[PDB]
Each structure stands twice: as structure tokens, then as C-alpha cells.
Amino acid sequence: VKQDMPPVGGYGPIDYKRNLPRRGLSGYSMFAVGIGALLFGYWSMMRWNRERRRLQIEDFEARIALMP
Amino acid sequence: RKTQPYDVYDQVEFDVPIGSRGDCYDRYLCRVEEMRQSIRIISQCLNKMPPGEI
């Protein structure tokens, strides 16, 4: 008999080509969400600094009424 | 391999990539697609292997 190592009846195909999923929410939508999150941070910054100026005027009233 | 097949390279089928400019970026990419063609040649060589003689 013959007992080499033969290819056993043919072998299935091996993938042989590039494959790129290329996703990632192309520049329109992600550009938009970047500017939108930036605007959200701006508006919260505006509100908090106005409240902070209120508090700073109260501390000014403290130093004024203390002084004499 | 395509011009003077000095062996059984003629009985296997592939396609060699060519660079487009002298830029070594092209040279690099040519090496990568030669690797992928090497995988194709190994696939066909396991497909059509004869159990002849050492």
C-alpha cells in the first residue's frame, strides 16, 4: 500500500482579499455631534458663571457691610 | 515566475502587483499584496498535490 500525506479529497477555500468595515459615523454626523456637545458645554458654562457672579456680588456686600 | 517558469509555477495561477510611482509606499503595498498572492499559491498547491515520489 501507499501511505504518503495526500490532500484529503480537496480543501475548502481560504479567504484571500482585503476587508475593511470602514464604519464610524462619517464626518457629517460626527462633526455635528462635536459642535453640538461643544454648544451644550457653552450653555451650561453661561448659566453657571451667571450664578457665580450672583454669589460674588453677595461676597462683595459682605466686605462692604463689614468694613467700618 | 511569469516569464521563465523554471518549475511547476506554470501550473498554478496568480497575479503579481505593480507599483504606480517610485514612492516606497507603493513598494510596501506591493509587498503586502504579494503576501496575499503567496497565500493563494499555497491554497492551490494544497488543492492539486500529487502523491507521487520523494
Image (tube, grey):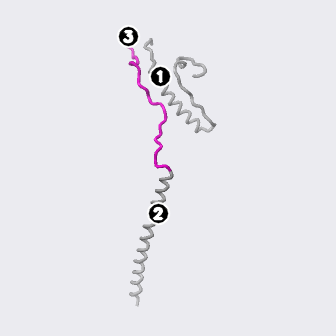
Label annotation for residue A43: none
The main secondary structure of the magenta stretch is loop
Amino acid of disc 1: Gln
Q: Which residues are magenta?
A: A1-26
Amino acid type of the residue tagged 2 in the rendering: Leu
Query: CA gap, disc 1 to disc 3?
Result: 23 Å
Of callouts 2 and 3, which one flags the residue occurring earlier in the amino acid sequence? 3
Q: Are marks 2 and 3 in contact (CB under 8 Å)?
A: no
Q: Which numbered disc covers residue A2? A: 3
Which element type, helix, strand or loop, lies under badge 1?
A: helix
Report which residue position mark 2 lands on. Answer: A39
Q: Are marks 2 and 1 on the same chain?
A: no
Which SS class for mark 3?
loop
- Quarter occupied by residue B15: top right
Residue lying at 44% horizontally and 63% vertically, measured from the top left: A40
Q: Are marks 2 and 3 on the same chain?
A: yes
Q: How packed is label 2: few (under 14 Cα within 10 Å), some, or many (20 or more)?
A: few
Q: Quadrant of the N terminus of chain B?
A: top right
Label 2 or label 3, whichever lies nearer to me, is 2
Please tell me whether residue A25 is drawn above or below residue A64 in the rendered image: above
Determine the residue positioned at 39% across, 87% down.
A65
Taking the spot 47% from the left edge, 37% from the top edge, the residue there is A19
Residue A42 drawn at (x, y percent): 46, 66
Q: Which residue is mark 1?
A: B44
| Alpha carbons under labels 2 and 3: distance apart | 78 Å
Q: Is the residue under label 3 in contact with that under label 1 (CB below 8 Å)?
A: no
Give the CA distance from mark 2 to mark 1: 59 Å
- In terms of secondary structure, where does tag 2 sit? helix
